[PDB]
Length: 328
Picture 1 (cartoon, helix red, strand yellow):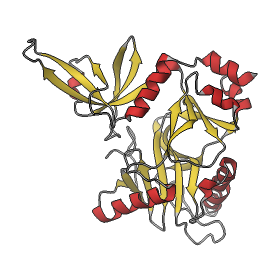
Picture 2 (cartoon, one colour):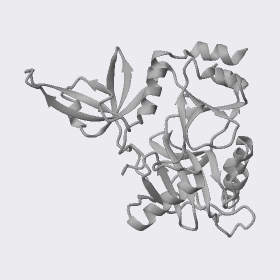
Picture 3 (cartoon, helix red, strand yellow):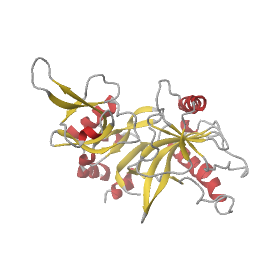
Picture 4 (tube, one colour):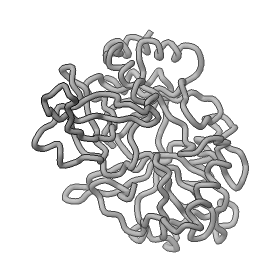
């Protein structure tokens, strides 16, 4: 959606609508991911419920703190070719980000695909953009995504953060020139995850150590404290009555890939303001509750993502309960 980062304004970053290169940057990301369908190829994590958590016993898992951020895959195809892709498949061209090849420090990266969030860090008085690299799909055409989540975590460290961090002590690369701060997200064993329950996080993520998968991953688990559970709906306000008379007018909430409305929202003075727009709602008191408009999404959550959140809110995993599952 046309806004790259919500609330922050960001240099060097300009949405790509050019008909020719758009369908291309999109094209290359499917192919790198093995994505058969249309839409954003990146792996989608599902909310932990009491049936999910049992999965943390059945194989090796890594944890990390989830900062609330905007999902972006980053395709490094060339010299000035650096693109971000959000969940909508919207593309953005980044200018001054340089990714030097590890062996030849003069040479530049091609056929690389990244995954991560854009997060807003606050250095007091001003908010600084950071892009955390939380996975890598492809490197120089080598299917690193087929390797071990620990193999790939190193790729990210050794093949990406390091070659850039050499030219960052050489004066050949100026970090005050670049659009945003490029970092990698730290992962731990579940053991130490408990301790994390004992920058800023609205929750935890649990990564299986397996090969990278695109699409819904029933096995990547997002845990979130039950009151912070939310869903992105298309809000369409329709005034209606049939022959059954009263002209009441109710806000209908919509999700992706379900045709009828998913829920209803009580109309208010304030709400009409964002209509036909996208709205993030928290669930409480047996009602969806408008919380903040979402300017970065041209699209609402998927019906399957939505149901997933409800599954979670009606059969929740409490902080303690998760604590007590990791511990012993």
